[PDB]
Image (cartoon, coloured by chain):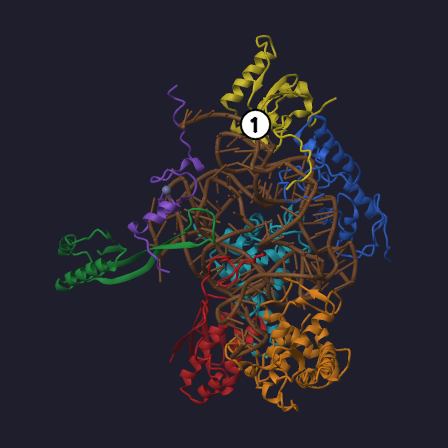
Chain colours: A red, B blue, C yellow, D cyan, E green, F orange, G purple, H brown
Amino acid sequence: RVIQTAGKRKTAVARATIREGKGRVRINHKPVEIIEPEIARFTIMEPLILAGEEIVSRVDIDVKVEGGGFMGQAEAARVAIARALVEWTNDMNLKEKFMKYDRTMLVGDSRRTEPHKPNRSTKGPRAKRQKSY
Amino acid sequence: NFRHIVRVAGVDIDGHKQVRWALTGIKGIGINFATMVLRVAGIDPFMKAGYLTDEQVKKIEEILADPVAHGIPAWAVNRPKDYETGKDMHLITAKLVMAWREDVNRLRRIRAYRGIRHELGLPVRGQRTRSNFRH
Amino acid sequence: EFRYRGYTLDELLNMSLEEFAKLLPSRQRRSLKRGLSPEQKKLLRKIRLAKKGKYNKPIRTHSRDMIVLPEMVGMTIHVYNGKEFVPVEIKEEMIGHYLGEFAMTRKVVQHGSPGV
Amino acid sequence: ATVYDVPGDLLVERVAKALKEVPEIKPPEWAPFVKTGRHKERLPEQEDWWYYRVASVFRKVYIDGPVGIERLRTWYGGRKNRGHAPEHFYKAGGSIIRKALQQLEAAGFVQKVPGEGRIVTPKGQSFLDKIATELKKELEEQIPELKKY
Amino acid sequence: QKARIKLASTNIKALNEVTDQIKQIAERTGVRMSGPIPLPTKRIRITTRKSPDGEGSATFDRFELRVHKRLVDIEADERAMRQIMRIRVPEDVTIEIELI
Amino acid sequence: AKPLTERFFIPKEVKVMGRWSVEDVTVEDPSLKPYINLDARILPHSHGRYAKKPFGKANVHIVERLINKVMRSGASHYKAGGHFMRREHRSIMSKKMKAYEVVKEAFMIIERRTKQNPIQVLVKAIENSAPRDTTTIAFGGIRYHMSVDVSPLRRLDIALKNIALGASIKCYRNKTTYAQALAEEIIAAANKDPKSFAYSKKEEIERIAQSSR
Amino acid sequence: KADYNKRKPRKFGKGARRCMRCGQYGPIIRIHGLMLCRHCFREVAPKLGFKKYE
RNA sequence: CCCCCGGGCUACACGCGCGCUACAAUGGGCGGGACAAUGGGAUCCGACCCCGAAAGGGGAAGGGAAUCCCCUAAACCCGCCCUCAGUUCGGAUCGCGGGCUGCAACUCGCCCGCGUGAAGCUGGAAUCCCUAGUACCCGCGUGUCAUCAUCGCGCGGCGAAUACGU
Ligand SMILES: [Zn+2]
């Protein structure tokens, strides 16, 4: 059987697919073990290392992620992978573990950008020019 | 087996530096023209200077004397379509200074805008002289 | 002796327009290819009449974007600066220049002392 | 086994090392006298940069094909130091890319779809995948997690 | 053998009207329709300065015109065209039909 | 160049950066024990989630706090080591990757030179760089410079800021690097050497405070 | 005599575009075939259908 | 008052406001590897092919815009050179040449190549903006527009420190 999941992180969207296999994970056609940089690789692989060998050596996961930066892509893929694993196992020990570790694995992140306002719109909403009187 | 300060045309360049960057101490030669001349001569610019054979120096000089004949495209040269002869040429320091001088002086001799700006010492091209350019 | 890129005057005079333009810089080549205008051409007629006989008067003009050609050497041309007609006697080393480079608009600034 | 199982760095390096046996791929007359784009300051420091550029163009036509010259220009361009003015992005030059692709064609590694771009041929595919197989067998010595792939 | 209908309007009342009309037509009659399909809304923004002079702090008015878009495919029966072309087409709606 | 077994590193156990443990680390100051987060993690990155809540900083791992301190430009609107440090385009501001790597190298050097756990080293350094100060209080109309005690959370903020500033100092317009500087600072503060900006300022602050008691 | 009274047909420049309501020359909204000054547009926008939507 | 030609608002011993670039290793260069969103588009956007070292030139599919185009962004990662110097930092000023727009480019436009290589080694008294996807850092679109963006209005990328007070 096959299962599909999704994940969102600011402006980025990931779709993951899990099925039976040997333990391979691919993100945009390439393995996760040669993902650079390390700060994104650990981000993506933290749920797998929490789930363990006896669960991950039996499945194969493929993620297609597009939009919004490499860090956002990595977070979205992490979310999708956690959700897919929890569903595929229908295990609750895993869910408790993930929740005590970081509840944004399964739950998402709702933060987006604030629109910009005049008096130096380019910089941001709250930043302004300086005066000297 | 490395000369620590070599003596190239007119100039006593430093041997402690690579050749491409040591040749840069000559007026009329940048890093890019230097790399060109060295790739034509057949020398490794990425090597510590000092082992600059007399014949290598002589060939560098042969090239600097007439670069176009030895390749060196006419668009990588310092003075294309010379006002008096055509004959795209590259000058190093001496008729370089003198050629700058002659250009400015011919501009002054006909009483042109640019010549008068050179005389008075003010910006020549188009700049706005109200807020900046304070002596 | 004067030599413009190898060639002398007597040669530049007999040379064509498309040959001469190959010696000039890009800007003047482009201008002279895109072509002259009614004003410039009436001035050229005036000059060709003056260099031989008919015209016996000074040559005045408002045309400052006009380019100095070899056929214009040996003449005097009065160019407008906005207020007055400045005389310019055209020397061989002017070739390739606009008439406005030899007729200035603003006066040299000699600063006084600041005020309040 | 495939181009997607190894990194682009080592693969481009090894492909450039291997392209030095194809006689149809030789640097042109003006190669040692030019920069790679207006956005550049200084010209290339390596003496065998042609082969690296050709190998990269080859891998790119593989990955993102069919593709033409302007998109490759956009990939190979970059940021510029404009002096006291702020920095802008500018695209690279086209003659290098054209000559690279024409050489790969003459060598029979790519072909042009009549109307949209250029793609690789089966022999080009085999070239790349064999080189990647070699490199992956080498890497498995260090990263034992790649064996399963 | 299918006819394609493009509807554009600044008001959704007329759009709901026309689309329910077409649905009733093609349902009471034997003829198939795919949709209606909502296309992305096209908005025109014009931002200008309030002050007629140059003094005072600068403040800006943001004006926005919105345009909604719908698509339908109707299978192009004969009775279909005859009963479709004669419908109340208000002035706040633009309609364009073509063949495929 | 970095070897490949370090460029492509794969962790298997829950460990800070996959390399260093926490169970062998022991705090001793009962005031700072409950604010030094020693949770077992792999990536110290919280993405700014714990800022809004008042005491939300006690849930952030020390390493993430240090990384965020190191993520700085230097000293604007005040002088440190005698001089302003304003970089403004060559600064690592909003670049957590570089700070991550700096801290990693520093930890490697510390382990190499000490043969202990760099987290234990950092813990003792904090313990020895946390100051136990003076302010201005008005007892009605009149104001006096008084001596008041400090809270653990502000102590921690002080110590981390001072360590990072010491590193930024010793790496200023010199041949030394930021990682080596941070390692030097940490070892010095842990073994109580006056060579350390942080221990120095701790002693100075307590010295002044003792006066105005 | 009668010729030195009418203006040339400019194709580009500030002097090729007017406002059909006020007659001004310079600050003309150019957006989407509209030819109105900023003042006149800000006065007659709702009658064309623009709104706040902020 | 209404039209045409030429000049000027671009003039510079100086005092000020707002900014851009820097005074370097928390970096410069070369070659490789990645990753967006907002908006706009008929004599307009122009993929694809061919010329050209570059700027640019010659043809031209399609597209009245969830269909085609502008559009493989930079900061970031990898390897090599440089190792604390007015330097491989910095990049003003000037010379020769090659192009575009336009009826016209000197006064008074923008781009490209080769050369040239000025101040500046962290900044007193004083003073500005910022409580979270905020501030700092990075680039892009659109308005103006025949040509010209260190500006205004907006867009996403990476992403903190402190206080929950007077
Ligand atoms: Zn009006």
* Ligand 1 quarter of the rendering: top left
Label 1: element kind: loop
Look at the image and tell me in which quarter the C terminus of chain A lies: bottom right
Q: Is residue B100 above or below residue F156?
A: above
Q: What residue do we see at 67% from left, 49% from top?
A: D32
Alpha-carbon neighbours of circle 1 within 10 Å: few (<14), some, or many (≥20)? few
Q: Position of residue B116 (x, y in %)?
A: 69, 31
- Numbered disc 1: what chain? C
Count of all numbered marks drawn on residues in the image: 1
Look at the image and tell me in which quarter the N terminus of chain A lies: bottom left
Q: What residue do we see at 53% from left, 54% from top?
A: D74
Query: Which residue reaches farthest front?
Result: F141
Q: What residue do we see at 59% from left, 56% from top?
A: A132
Location of residue D134 (image quadrant): bottom right
Residue A116 or A79: which is nearer the viewer?
A116
Q: Position of residue A120 (x, y in %)?
A: 51, 57
Q: Position of residue E54 (x, y in %)?
A: 47, 47
Confirm if mark 1 falls within 8 A of ligand 1. no
Residue A26 left/right relative to F182 = left
The answer to whether residue G16 shows anywhere in this view is yes
Residue D56 or F184: which is nearer the viewer?
F184
Residue C43 or F34: which is nearer the viewer?
F34
Residue D132 left/right relative to A84 = right
Q: Position of residue A129 (x, y in %)?
A: 54, 58
Q: Which residue is mark 1?
A: C65
The answer to whether residue D117 shows anywhere in this view is no
* Amino acid at the residue labelled 1: Asp
